[PDB]
Image (spheres, coloured by chain):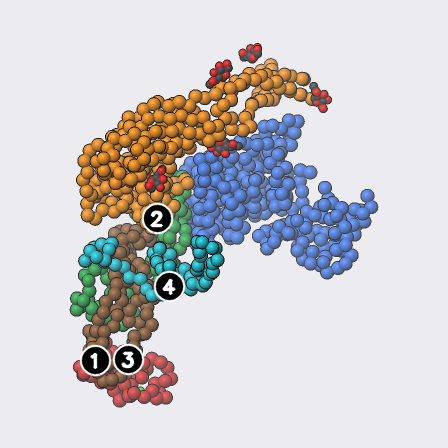
Chain colours: A blue, B green, C brown, D orange, E cyan, F red
Amino acid sequence: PVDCVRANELCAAESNCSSRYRTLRQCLANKECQAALEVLQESPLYDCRCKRGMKKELQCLQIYWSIHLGEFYEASPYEPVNHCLDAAKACNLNDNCKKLRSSYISICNREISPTERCNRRKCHKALRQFFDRVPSEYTYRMLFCSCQDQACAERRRQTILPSCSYEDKEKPNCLDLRGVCRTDHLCRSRLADFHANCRASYQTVTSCPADNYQACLGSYAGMIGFDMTPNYVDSSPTGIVVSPWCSCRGSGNMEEECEKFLRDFTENPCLRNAIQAFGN
Amino acid sequence: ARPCGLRELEVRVSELGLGYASDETVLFRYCAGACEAAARVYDLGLRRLRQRRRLRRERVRAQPCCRPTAYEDEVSFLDAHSRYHTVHELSARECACV
Amino acid sequence: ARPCGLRELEVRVSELGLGYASDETVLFRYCAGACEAAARVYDLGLRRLRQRRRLRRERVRAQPCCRPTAYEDEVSFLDAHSRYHTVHELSARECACV
Amino acid sequence: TSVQANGSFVRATVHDYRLVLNRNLSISENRTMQLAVLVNDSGVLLLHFNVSVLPVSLHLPSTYSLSVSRRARRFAQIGKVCVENCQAFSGINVQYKLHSSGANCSTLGVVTSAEDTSGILFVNDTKALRRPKCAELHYMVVATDQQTSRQAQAQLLVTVEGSYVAEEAGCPLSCAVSKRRLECEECGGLGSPTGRCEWRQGDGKGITRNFSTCSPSTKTCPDGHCDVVETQDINICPQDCLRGSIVGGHEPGEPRGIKAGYGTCNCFPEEEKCFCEP
Amino acid sequence: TSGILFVNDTKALRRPKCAELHYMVVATDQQTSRQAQAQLLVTVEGSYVAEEAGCPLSCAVS
Amino acid sequence: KRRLECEECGGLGSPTGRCEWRQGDGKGITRNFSTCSPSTKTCPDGHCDVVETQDINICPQD
Ligand SMILES: *[C@@H]1O[C@H](CO)[C@@H](O)[C@H](O)[C@H]1NC(C)=O
Ligand SMILES: *[C@@H]1O[C@H](CO)[C@@H](O)[C@H](O)[C@H]1NC(C)=O
Ligand SMILES: *[C@@H]1O[C@H](CO)[C@@H](O)[C@H](O)[C@H]1NC(C)=O
Ligand SMILES: *[C@@H]1O[C@H](CO)[C@@H](O)[C@H](O)[C@H]1NC(C)=O
Ligand SMILES: *[C@@H]1O[C@H](CO)[C@@H](O)[C@H](O)[C@H]1NC(C)=O
Ligand SMILES: [Ca+2]
Ligand SMILES: [Ca+2]
């Protein structure tokens, strides 16, 4: 398994491979394209992955999407691997979780104007830095904690602090938000990571591919801190339905694909069964 | 006779007396002990001048009290009414006998 | 009461009571005054936990005592036996409430 | 939107056409127009708009008869100068100035808040008010403008009324230094026109906006707003205008200030520090 | 026809940052504009001790 | 520091198992300073021999 950084390392160590890589990069960014394709289908850049929380993930993804030829699903460039009161108490007794926790809270709970509720990009940056370098027995315990009443569900909803990040003035079109997320490098890669690990299945007994709860939970929590950042819909104790901040309105004749894209978050038996079995 | 250093204790938020209506528990680091062999020539001379009343009869301190050096930065929590709070400089990180 | 800072004095060598036999006069500086604008959230939490007796019954400090930050280097003098003597750290150089 | 056809629910588009300005219109516009709008649904639709831009009169009531006590201190609010339509201006800057008649008894000043576009009297000098010579003062309040130089003017009569009593020996310079109730009213700070500081008393309901404190004016200092008068020199109202640190369970204001506190809250503006404790 | 140094501010002398100050003393003229200039190095030296509680503002009050 | 706690406890360097107390004079800064030593012939001797310099807990006052 060769990641794209070392694939560029072996690419820059050779003359023909670098020539065909820069040739295809000048093609994308007939006959010049097809020869570069039939050469670089044997490159170490061909089928290179990236890692979660690796150093210079952005360059790895910019290299990986550079060789990609120009669509509901895409290939993931990654390695295919009171209760909530007690979760917060287990965080605040460690030192690494406490510092970054107070970091994203003291950033995201700063009202600026009576119009601007909070700063968006710094709050997303703090949430990404929280959900990258914290051990996952702390994140999953605070974000997924089994509740029986309304106050526990409200604490669990308020954990990613949706008053700044999740909600907006309007609910835009889900397809437009998908286009915005697929414009950016990082959000498109996290969305493909979520699509590769959290589809429904008719063959496996838990409707999840490879019967892997862990990959679908990591593909869920890796979408926090982007524009396609989901959260719960209400403070329901047992009813657990996640959703991004959009809706099916404004769809036109593209209504069915919008509904099918939204049913990945609203009506996934794989993700809901994974959350329920993790709560058990 | 124990050396002055960090002492840790798990405490409620509402037992800290800061009026935050919350029941979470955080760890608390405070400086505790007794400074005995830290007296200097400054300390002895100032004590003797208090014994001779050359002083201008003010508030002075002629025993080295053990205090924190640098505090922890931030502790954030949520209340009983779904609203976060960020307390700056709650516990100590280093204890020095000055 | 007055705020804490430097106060000067001029005292004899043998009036320090250290056993020296001389009559020269040295310029003794000291930190004096009151700390009322230096209590922090740490101080309030420590005071409240002393009130609820959750403490392990040790010696703590919930009033920030004003001590010198640094100290002066040397004091050189001569005595009744005609012998030079240099003493380190006799007075202060900067005051702060800690 | 969802409309019914035969007991069903289908959806359709409701387009909204609104009409938006492009710049700050000045006062001197006295026009009217009709605007025509083409709509192409590529079916060809026409819309109209009767717009009427009417100018604004800027006259004021002519004489603002008012008084001031002799015990007052520097930077204390007295009265409000404003246009007849105070809360009508949005994008027109209106500034207020003074012209003393004798040019020897300069005591008062006017600064303009651009929220209400209105001016507030403030005591600038103590000695000129302290003199028994300059006891009834006549000012020409001139209401000016920035964009188009239409202006107006008016009369200001003010009477220097009362007696003078010295303050106490150990008084500080601001009202908020006191902590109990008695030492607040038995000493005079800076911003009050009464010469003494006022005490408002809160509640025991935890971290509230109703925090017990000592202010110059109970209608001005714990108002939740830092106006133009308080922001001149930071000793007047520290509990609405500071940029500093707070010791105690609280919540700070949105640009600045104390939004909510617990217990009694005093402030040292010389160190930009505040304390809240029962 | 000579100039005398005077302390204008206390706080800037009180700061430990502005401890060695370099000024361009410019000797000017009124009638004919021939002028010159020179260097001024000054060192902020010593310690600071607060005064007493009941002090007046002038020396001659005592 | 006092006399009783010196002899009612045993330190390191003494072959007697208890510490010895020598008592000085009130003549100011003297060589005859009252102290608690392991041996009154070895520790306040004015000389740091080979035995005391092995581990520095034996005779700190030499
Ligand atoms: C605006 O123009 C009309 C035109 O007849 C005039 O009557 C009116 O007085 C003008 N407005 C003002 C404020 O003078
Ligand atoms: C509306 O747009 C279409 C598309 O260009 C154009 O052919 C048509 O002429 C337009 N309608 C009018 C009234 O110009
Ligand atoms: C707008 O102006 C035209 C001009 O005559 C007039 O016919 C029409 O009635 C006006 N609109 C309304 C709503 O009065
Ligand atoms: C319009 O008026 C407001 C009023 O304060 C001012 O802040 C703004 O800069 C003005 N803008 C233009 C384009 O004149
Ligand atoms: C207040 O008085 C000072 C000094 O006399 C002066 O500089 C200032 O301009 C006055 N304030 C106003 C608003 O004119
Ligand atoms: Ca105010
Ligand atoms: Ca020896």
Query: Which of these two is toward me, F41 or D111?
Result: D111
Image vertical order of residue E26 relative to residue D51, above or below = below
The residue pinned by badge 2 equals: D272
Alpha carbon separation for disc pair 1 and 2: 50 Å
Tag of residue C85: 3
Q: Amino acid at mark 4?
A: Val
How crowded pointer 4 is (Cα within 10 Å; few <14, some 14-19, many 20+) is rated as some
Furthest toward the right, the residue is A31
The residue pinned by badge 4 equals: E44
Alpha carbon separation for disc pair 3 and 1: 11 Å
How crowded pointer 3 is (Cα within 10 Å; few <14, some 14-19, many 20+) is rated as few
Residue A111 % position (x, y) = 44, 40
Q: Is residue A48 left or right of residue C89?
A: right
Q: Nearer the viewer, mark 2 or mark 4?
A: 4
Tag of residue A99: none
Q: Is residue D44 left or right of residue F49?
A: right
Secondary structure beneath label 3: strand
Q: Amino acid at mark 1?
A: Ala
Q: Are marks 4 and 1 on the same chain?
A: no
Residue D7 % position (x, y) = 58, 15
How crowded pointer 2 is (Cα within 10 Å; few <14, some 14-19, many 20+) is rated as some
Q: Amino acid at mark 3?
A: His
